[PDB]
Image (tube, rainbow, N blue to C red):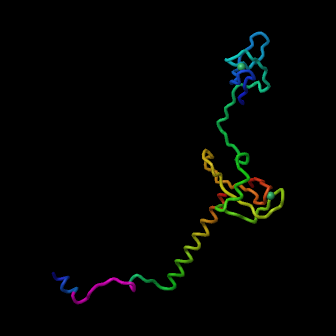
Amino acid sequence: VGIRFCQECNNMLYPKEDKENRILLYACRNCDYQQEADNSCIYVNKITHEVDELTQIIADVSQDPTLPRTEDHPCQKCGHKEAVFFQSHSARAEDAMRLYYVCTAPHCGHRWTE
Amino acid sequence: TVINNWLLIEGHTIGIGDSIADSKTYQDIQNTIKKAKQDVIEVIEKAH
Ligand SMILES: [Zn+2]
Ligand SMILES: [Zn+2]
């Protein structure tokens, strides 16, 4: 999945085949540094990719003066009443007009979606 | 010619009295507008 780098030349490690022990080795093209990986999966491609933005929503959006606010949706963690909300606010999100919420209490930053 | 010289008797105009409605009509229009805005709000709530 991710990119792993050689410790000698600090270049990308390409996958190379070990035709003796039937094992996967990551080797670079600059030096002869070898490795054994734990992912065991070279490549992964998901075409749905309906990523939940709760990973990508920052908790600092609560300081936006231009966002709507509601008090009928208390925070799950700290029980604070006021909570900002907004839509997907991102492209490649199909057409879902689902709402997203962020707690406005400082240092809480709870970001959920009912 | 005939219609113009007769129109010199009847006359024609356009004014605010011709562009103003009645109180009952104003109430009807405002009611309809409020109902439509409420329905739009309901649709938005269902979408959310
Ligand atoms: Zn290397
Ligand atoms: Zn909270």
Q: Nearer the viewer, residue A45 or B26?
A: A45
Q: Is residue A74 above or below residue A29?
A: below
Outermost residue to the top:
A20
Asked which quadrant contains residue A62, the reply is: bottom right
Q: Which residues are magenta?
A: B8-17
Residue at (22%, 85%) from the top-left corner? B7
Q: Is residue A71 above or below residue A14?
A: below
Residue at (59%, 72%) from the top-left corner? B35
**A89 relative to A106 in the view: left or right:** left
Q: Is residue B21 magenta?
A: no
Query: Which of the four quarters of the rendered structure image does ligand 2 lie in?
Result: bottom right
Image coords of residue A108 (percent x, y): 80, 55
**A99 relative to A23 in the view: left or right:** left
**B4 relative to A52 in the view: left or right:** left
Outermost residue to the right:
A78
Image coords of residue B11 (percent x, y): 26, 87
Count of numbered tags: 0
Asked which quadrant contains residue B16, the reply is: bottom left
Which of the image's four quarters has the N terminus of chain A?
top right
Outermost residue to the front:
A8
Outermost residue to the bottom:
B9
